[PDB]
Image (spheres, coloured by chain):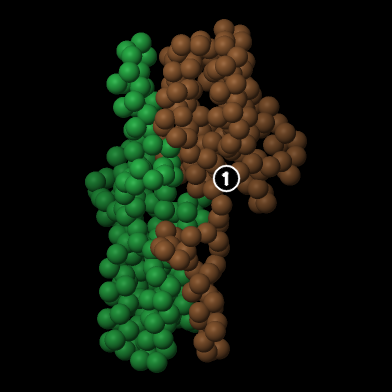
Chain colours: A brown, B green
Amino acid sequence: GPTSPGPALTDWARVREELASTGPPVVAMPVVIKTEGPAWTPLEPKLITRLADTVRTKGLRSPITMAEVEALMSSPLLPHDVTNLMRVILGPAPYALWMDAWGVQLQTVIAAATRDPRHPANGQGRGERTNLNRLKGLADGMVGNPQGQAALLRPGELVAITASALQAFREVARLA
Amino acid sequence: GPTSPGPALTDWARVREELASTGPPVVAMPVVIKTEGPAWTPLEPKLITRLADTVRTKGLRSPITMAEVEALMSSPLLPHDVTNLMRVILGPAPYALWMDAWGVQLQTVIAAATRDPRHPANGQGRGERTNLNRLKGLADGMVGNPQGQAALLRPGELVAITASALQAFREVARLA
């Protein structure tokens, strides 16, 4: 990633390499993790407003709306984002239905998550297994912390999260 | 912060404003958090190598080293950073002493943290109180996750963390 201009996170990979190519005594021994690649995608305000507009005018049960939401929810999103996105398009009343539907959808994910310790929502470690709270961005450190969510949620969970969001949306757009 | 070029985190502040300046029905009602301002500072590889060089040549008990480390540890750092910084300058053997000394130093912080629920290391909430593991970047989600640390640690904790690191360093540079 962009490390030439400025390193948001100390680029310890470079430090490693340096120390190495200079003297053997001790050396390139700093712990080089390299957690990289943001699997979530941020939404563009203007694209969100036009979705609101479309949901306003064309309706909600409208195929246009479904089409435009579907597309916008093809990329992984953080719990914070789905939540806010929905709070804006759905409105106070249906948002609740969605919240409910979304939780149900998420629950079946906690199954394929349990059924298989190899599910994309889980990690390598033994504790690294998703949970309803994680998926909802309610897990400790995620609550009201999108920055926190971006750092803790695994790509596999983001995909689950977003698909569920999209399902529950259809569930509510039609069954309403 | 930079939101004109591209919004790393969905800029919901803008979305709020839009919806508002257009139609009253529902409106600018997305939850706008705005967690901002990184209180930690990333280290520049070259500056780290020269510190290694200085620690190598000039020594460790050297005042030059103390001078150059002091300066470099005047800005808040993440547990990951202090740890790696030290692992590089201190070497296998003393690093252990430092680890030990650093923990002791951190422990007295857990006191002023407990003594006062208004300590900078604590938050507003009732659970938002620091702990040895947080300060060490061992808290869940911080382990091997500098990105995670940057999102969870509070500025007040970063200052504690870095000062302690600096103390424990002096503790080890002299008492060795």
Is residue B140 left or right of B109 when viewed as pictured? right
**Numbered disc 1: secondary structure:** loop
Left or right: B16 as drawn, with respect to A114: left
Q: State the residue at coordinates (54%, 77%).
A: A17
- Give the residue at x 24% y 46%: B118
Residue in the picture at 57% in, 10% down: A61
For the residue pair B46 and B92, the one nearer the viewer reads as B46
In percent of width and height, residue A92 lies at 43, 14
Q: Say if A72 sits above or below B37 in the image.
A: above
At x 49% / y 69%, what residue is drawn? A12
Q: How many numbered marks are there? A: 1
- Give me the chain letter of mark 1: A
- Residue A146: x %, y % from top left: 44, 39
Can residue B27 be seen at all in this image of the molecule? yes
In the rendered image, the quadrant that contains the C terminus of chain A is top right
Name of the residue lying farthest toward the top: A176
Q: Residue B151 appears at what percent x and percent y?
A: 42, 49
x, y percent for residue A125: 66, 51
Q: Which residue is mark 1?
A: A39
Nearest the camera: B141 or A156? A156
* Crowd band around label 1 with a 10 angstrom C-alpha radius: few (<14), some (14–19), many (20+): some
Amino acid marked by disc 1: Ala
Q: Is residue A164 above or below residue A155?
A: above
Residue A132 in view (yes/no)? no
Q: As rendered, which of B14 and A136 lies closer to the eye?
A: B14
Apparent side of residue A84 relative to residue A16 in the rendered image (left or right): left
